Structures are given as C-alpha cells and as structure tokens.
Length: 50
Length: 51
Image (cartoon, rainbow over all chains, first blue to last red; front, side):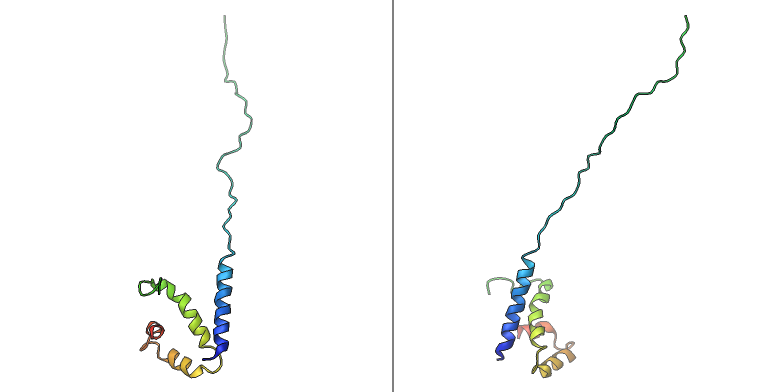
C-alpha cells in the first residue's frame, strides 16, 4: 500500500466533516402584522328644515 | 459494521465513492483506473466497491 494516499483521504474526509459542522441556521424574518395609520370619519350630506 | 451497510439508500453512495475515486486519481494507479472507467457498463461501481 502507498501510505501517502491514506493520509490524503483522511485529511479530505476530516476537512469535509469540519466544513459540514460549521453551517449555522439563523433566520431573521419580519412579522405579518401591518402598521396602522390615523384616519378621520367623514360627514355625509344632510338637510335640516323646521 | 454497526450502521449504513446493505440497507443504506442509493443516495449515500456519492459520499462513499468519493474517497475511492480520489485514490484512483493519484500517480501509479492509472492502469486500474483506466480499466475501471472503460468498462463501467459490464462491471458497475457498486460491485467494485463491494469487492
């Protein structure tokens, strides 16, 4: 056996495992709530007589 | 022998085969590599790996 291929294979598999073990899962999504604004009731036309 | 032997799904073969085809690409292994890649249809990768 060529002892220099085993070392390279071990290094490669160790690098793969180390790379796979650093990935993090973090999400910073917003919320579905809607910001509300001010409003004023409007007046419908009316007629007054006595 | 404890896990991932015969029952392993075909999806796991990519990881296992990578080391073998990395070993086959070094100097001094060109005869076996050529014979293996030339006749993959008759002797597949899975039977070679099992052997």
